[PDB]
Image (cartoon, rainbow over all chains, first blue to last red; front, top):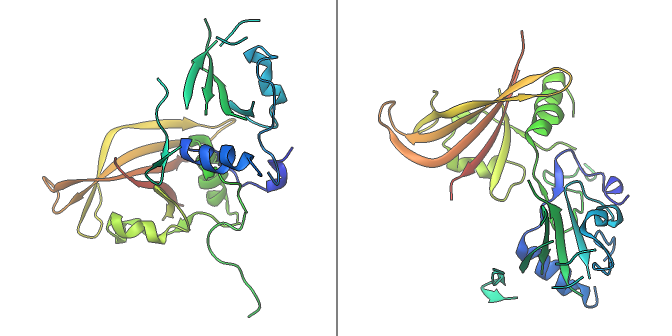
Length: 110
Length: 139
């Protein structure tokens, strides 16, 4: 478990912004992670509900590098520094995927 | 002396890690722990009611859009903090109850001072000696 070894103080979480995800992770995946908090997974060898286990960490959301495949799956222009470089999906279920090698947040709703 | 470290984060926190505490954390891990007597120090002790809200950000050891403080209607600097909406209860197993109270800053006398966007959430424990406050600006 990587999070424990970061000696993270009570209340310190991973609340990344759509901008940070772009530049610091996705962009950094070309030639880029000292401690790879989010790993690779072929996200569609799977049904939404078991991914959390194979995420390296997470309480309520999970992040992965990756009508598509027991079931199947408006995006807004993200800009950084006023210069541009995300898509929402559903599995019908509380199972939501955020799409940004691509970077995805998965979480359960309501 | 030889090096003594400075206010902030040492933590080499991986890009993406805020301090987004939950109401339970602020209660248990901070407010309660302070109130018990602890000490990686993270939340500034400050008399909030000494200062205008906009001078505050610089006094928190960190914070991008908000600032936590421990502090020992009411009146502060050029104005006054106004209680708001309804206080919200927080209960931690097995025991402690704390109240989040919401307040807004007004410049001037009491009535009828002129409203601002300065918001304060105040976390206080209930017992039979501090408060914990989030300060931030609306919008």
